[PDB]
Image (tube, rainbow, N blue to C red):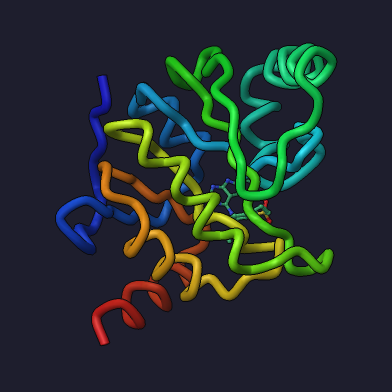
Length: 168
Ligand SMILES: CC(C)[C@H](Nc1ncnc2[nH]c(-c3cnn(CC(N)=O)c3)cc12)c1ccc2c(c1)S(=O)(=O)CCC2
């Protein structure tokens, strides 16, 4: 149904909210939920682990079957799989993990995958344990995504920092 509520409008197509992406998916029922995935689709922690746990491991089992037939993704790449109880579809997107020596330029490639879907609920790619500067990740999102993107950022301190930096 895509009923998003409580979002701050940053640009004509980019919205942001201090929220847990799992709680937003349950409330919104979006057509597309974005997962901050790794190349083998192993959802062992962070945003991916939270989404997987909310599908009671159904997402991991489907992900394993996809990798068996198609092999791993590339950094900056994506795949569309079932959204299970959270969404119609899950778009698994691999942003670079600069904490593992991956190239930050690939974050543009990662956000470009959003352009194939008219409206998506997403996290801030490559932020948290992936090591990218969150302010930079929001700027790449604003400059690269043209479709309607609702960003859920589960940290009030980071949310206010991103909003102040964007309004500067
Ligand atoms: C910047 C950070 C605040 C943000 N976190 C999140 N942003 C939005 N929705 C979230 N839900 C949870 C969560 C964590 N636990 N639970 C309960 C559960 N049952 O697991 C829900 C965390 C989360 C963030 C954004 C991007 C990435 C990561 C973290 S990561 O996982 O460290 C590496 C991949 C890229």
